[PDB]
Amino acid sequence: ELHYIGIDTAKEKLDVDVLRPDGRHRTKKFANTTKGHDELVSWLKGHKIDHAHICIEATGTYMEPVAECLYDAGYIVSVINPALGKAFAQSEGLRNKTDTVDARMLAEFCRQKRPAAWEAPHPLERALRALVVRHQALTDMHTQELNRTETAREVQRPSIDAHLLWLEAELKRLEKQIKDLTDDDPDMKHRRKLLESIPGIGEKTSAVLLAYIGLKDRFAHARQFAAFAGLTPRRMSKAGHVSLRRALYMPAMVATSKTEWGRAFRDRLAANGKKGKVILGAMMRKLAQVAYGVLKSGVPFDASRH
Amino acid sequence: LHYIGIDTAKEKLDVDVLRPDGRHRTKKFANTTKGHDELVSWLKGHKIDHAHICIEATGTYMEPVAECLYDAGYIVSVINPALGKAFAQSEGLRNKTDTVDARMLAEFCRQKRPAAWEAPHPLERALRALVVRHQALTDMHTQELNRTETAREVQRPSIDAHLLWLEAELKRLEKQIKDLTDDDPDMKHRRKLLESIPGIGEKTSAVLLAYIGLKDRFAHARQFAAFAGLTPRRYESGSSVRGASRMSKAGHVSLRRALYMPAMVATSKTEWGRAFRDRLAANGKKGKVILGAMMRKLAQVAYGVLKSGVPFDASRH
Amino acid sequence: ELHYIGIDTAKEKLDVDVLRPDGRHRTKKFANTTKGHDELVSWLKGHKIDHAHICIEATGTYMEPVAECLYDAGYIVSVINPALGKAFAQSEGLRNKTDTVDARMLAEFCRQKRPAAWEAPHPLERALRALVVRHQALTDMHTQELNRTETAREVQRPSIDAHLLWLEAELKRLEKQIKDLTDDDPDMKHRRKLLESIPGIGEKTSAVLLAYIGLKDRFAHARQFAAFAGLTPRRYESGSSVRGASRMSKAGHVSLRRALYMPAMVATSKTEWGRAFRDRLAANGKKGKVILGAMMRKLAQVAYGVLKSGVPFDASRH
Amino acid sequence: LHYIGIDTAKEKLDVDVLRPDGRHRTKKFANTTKGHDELVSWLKGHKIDHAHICIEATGTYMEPVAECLYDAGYIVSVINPALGKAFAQSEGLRNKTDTVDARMLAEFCRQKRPAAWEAPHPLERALRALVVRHQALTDMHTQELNRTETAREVQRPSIDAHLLWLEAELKRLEKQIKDLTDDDPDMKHRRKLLESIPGIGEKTSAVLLAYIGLKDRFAHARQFAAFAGLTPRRMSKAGHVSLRRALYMPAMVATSKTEWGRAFRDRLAANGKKGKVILGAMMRKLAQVAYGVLKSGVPFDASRH
RNA sequence: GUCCGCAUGCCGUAUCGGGCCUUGGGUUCUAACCUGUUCUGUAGAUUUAUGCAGCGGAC
RNA sequence: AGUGAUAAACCGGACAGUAUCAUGGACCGGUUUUCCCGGUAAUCCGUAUUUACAAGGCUGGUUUCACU
DNA sequence: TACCACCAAGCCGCCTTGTATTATCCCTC
DNA sequence: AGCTCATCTGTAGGCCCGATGGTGGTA
DNA sequence: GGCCATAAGTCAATCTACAGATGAGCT
DNA sequence: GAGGGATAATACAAGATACTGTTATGGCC
Ligand SMILES: [Mg+2]
């Protein structure tokens, strides 16, 4: 006795499809609102559905309320990468693509694949990643305006210089807001110190790594976390968080250039005859693994191991 | 019930059994009559009485082993290679640049539980073989036709000699097809029904029989249209993603190829065709769009007329 | 007597290649600095070169000072579209040494084609376009931060809301700076009112149009200004077989093309003469965006027409 | 001197004359033996007895009119169409029509002053035609060979019957080519020089001679390498594919089996070059050495390499 | 010999940007008609090849 | 930077192909959403040959070596 | 003790002209 | 003075150029 | 003097949902 | 009454798997 539910999410609506143990489908549309989420739970209890595994494609942040609602209702929620769903639909031989089809396709995804259960991240983890991605957003905007000074007309410059001062201030404000967040929590304070002990990783990179690694050891292996960033070869897969991947490139250079263990790594690969960026790609992968390793070890970085 | 996947190749087979408990027995074999008997014996050795084998439709290299296991007394499924690739990509994020392993096909078989494959009737195999040979030589004839336009004088003897040969051969095959369909009383009758449709003649009917077959495999005419890849492909999500509808093309190309000129003959110089054309033309559709739609219609009517078992009735349209 | 010079510009260094009437070359590289620009002029006068036609590629802000320098030093300066430059290099050979267009190639471009002479913009024209493109940059960033509010985390919202305020303030400030520019000059003040008289054009669109049309009427026909914005269809007819389909060329300033879209949408919807234009097109098998693309072209063409006429918009003419 | 630009079509012509004073004169003609005789007369109508005519290398529809005007007494230039298009994009940014292109070729002619086109010798034209036909039948013979691999048994009589026909025809042309060569004393000797190179045999010698021709129409051997599209820009590939493809198998036979070829392979292998990069390099070399050997007029000498 | 450890070797070309240039074609002929699908964006998801080598532990 | 010489050295990833596979979204009656059952030669959603085919064109960069 | 300067840097053919298929209807020997 | 509401499949080319972060080494 | 093997054989993340602009008539 | 010729359509994009031949020469018989 286990139902398999599939929810295709939109901004406004929720298309739901319940696959019963007998094999027949029940479907109903709902509003993607706090009210319409309570309507969904009531409609499941209406049909006497107590145990169910619910599958839902990671679709912006429109699925996040209902995923947490159904988790709290006491169901098994799985939030799948939508690339998998796309591939599954093709494997299921489906020609047309509609919302009703997708909700059914997700129900069958749930039954066949039996995906891993989804856990809502800790409030601190959610806060930290929010600040970190906001910080990258301002940096990008600061870089836009900093490029413009190069070829700016003299009537444009007062505006550009003014904007740069604002952006530089706001950037510092967040950096403190981040520091306050990690310093308050005893665990994050300690874990961040461990990351900064790695030569090549500083204030900025340590925050990014904590945002994606989290409080607890959610990864079982170092190579898993490296793969999660899209750093493991397939050429690099690039099948992982781009914000995590981009944050490691400049750490990789200062490591391979101005550290002992970095130059040691650089020279070894240089000997075998690797190009500059190939070595950097490799060092990005290594920094990721070492970062996860240092945290699980729970003791400062030790160069002797490398 | 065990689940087996076979990664077929020209020279080697690669086999992966999945036991009910969940352990993998694996062995490679030669893709030969000997190595097919080795497989059956190896399966029978490990006390594998009932199993569901899944094979990719790679080509003619997988056909003997599929027949061997069918005879041995197993459930053989022969899957569209695109489904296998898509399945591998649904199993992981980074399986794009990877082969579909025998293990993957066993998992495919367990999860999907695909339909059982049936070997075609020897007569159906012969017909489809002749029909695609006929298409092959038409293409070659067309090549040489195009060459006559801009030929040099020293080349023309060679091109003209080839054209004679190709026309003689095309004519020989057309008789060999006619003799095949006439000899069998079922095909003779079913062909006559297809030709009753206005827009469908001697060549198209042979192509339709080659893919419809003796038995009525398709439950609904809709499905035979989908089989040819002639149905539109909807692409809709939320209130933003709005992909324009287009011909799916996810079906037999040999079929889809054969229906275009019929569609053009239908919509142009036929009562029921013009009627269809005008209605869509009024609704504001392009010329080639109307043909694409008529192609789907002909396929759908072709199966409909056979399913009825009576000649084409214009009143129904 | 007339020499043909080509200058291949870079950030730091100039690369000059004189072509003599006889056919021999003179080559000398210079620094791309105020000193090196005066050094260039002296060097040309050194070799008794008073009459010459200089050809430079339009690569941005590194080639502007030297183009000014030579124009003032009494020479015919042509500033060519780099797309023309590359196409010329490919017409000279099939397997060219490099894909780059060197100074020698530019000297040759100048000789064979005798391109049109480049006139330096008026300080006010150059200032107005500077402010207008700055305004469009801040509008883009404002739109970025607007989109973010939709899906923002609550810890992020204070930062986004704060930025939006700054951007909105800056945009108001900059719009006033534009208004004060045009209202000071009696020429620009008059021309702006003539533009705004057109239904579907207001304060923002008028400034963009003035920025690209300028003080004087450089275009002979109004169709040419529509082409300058990249709003004219692109035909691809060849022989009998090769017949494609007409789409917008988009071969022109994006700043103009982006500025006219919402005006066109206002015109066809609310204004009488626009609605009239929409309907006649809509009668034929013409889709919504196709009508907008058409109205965009029309608005540009009317915008120029009105300024050339020198009298406010008159609905009777449409 | 007048600058005339002919835009060619299957049926019609679009002539555009540009006078020294700088005024256009347009007049259409039919692309026929009659309409070519009209053109000659109409030019002499406006007292044009000395002009440079520019026309795109467009199919074979411009071959008669080019031969006509060459015989009439004009400087005919037949330009690569890729150049023409590039020139059109250098003049403007917009629109592509027949009326534009006819006028455009007059401007091309004036500014560029392109090299004069010379009609091939009948034998050069015949040999090329046979060699081109021979490739067409080889490509068809391969199709039917591939088809035997996976053929059904009812198809197999048809495929085998076709192969026999194709093999008979290939053998026939190879003789027709050999007869053409052995008759002409020049081609007979020229081909013998080509075959003397280790790595070039019956097949390749005919292909090379088809594109080199009777006269030494290239100044240097490195020019002929460029004409095949074998020179690095990665290979440009800006040349005859028929000439290019013919050298790949000779290149393998050279680098693998011949003494001078192995030497070449080894030297690049020492520097650390990939398999196909060495083949790419040897293709260029065979082309260069082929032309060199003909210039010399002396059988291949290994010493030089 | 098997299984399990690994911040190990082998494999690895990051992510974002900025500025500037653009003087149609046909017609009943240039503020007319025919021909015309703007310019930019935003957010989220991603758990090993441990595949093969080493090195270590347990039985 | 020209001109002449070059069968040398450096720079070099050719072309053409073949076979095979493919059971719509839905609509119309029941049930009283879908699912499921029955029906579909009708209506709405369709730019064929998941690459249609043919012919033609293509006069190197540099380093040595001479002469300006 | 706060401030400055490096650290890495790949992409791979273009053009111009043409035409066939099949089945049904209409015209001529 | 303020608010709504008009469009919905995707497809121009070229040339000049810069930032990121975290060390070890300066003033 | 007629047959037969055989030399060569790189590629550049994937998805899923979403939004703004400007100017004129209306409120 | 039967056989041959002409016309209908025109912007293009977007699925997978398995596989082969070319030529010329030094090896064989
Ligand atoms: Mg969805």
Image (cartoon, coloured by chain):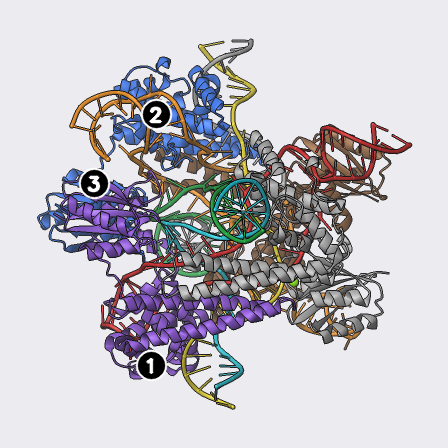
Chain colours: B brown, C purple, D blue, E red, F orange, G green, H cyan, I yellow
What SS does tag 2 mark?
helix
Residue type at numbered disc 1: Ser
Relative image position of residue F15 (x, y in whole percent):
45, 36
Mark 3 to mark 2: distance in Å? 35 Å
Query: Would you call the spot at circle 2 few (<14 residues within 10 Å), some (14-19), or many (20 or more)?
Result: some
Mark carried by residue D288: 2
Nearer mark to the viewer, of 3 and 2: 3
In the rendered image, the residue lying farthest to the left is D47
In the picture, the quarter occupied by the C terminus of chain C is: bottom left
Q: Please state which of residues C81 and E23 is positioned toward the viewer in this rendering.
A: C81
Chain letter for mark 1: C
Q: For the residues marked 2 and 1, what is the alpha-carbon distance in whole angstroms?
A: 71 Å
Image spot of residue D156 (x, y percent): 58, 33
Q: Which mark is residue B147?
A: none
Q: Using the image, name the chain to which the residue with label 2 belongs.
A: D
Residue assigned mark 1: C197
| Residue at the disc numbered 3 | C26
* Badges 2 and 1, same chain: no
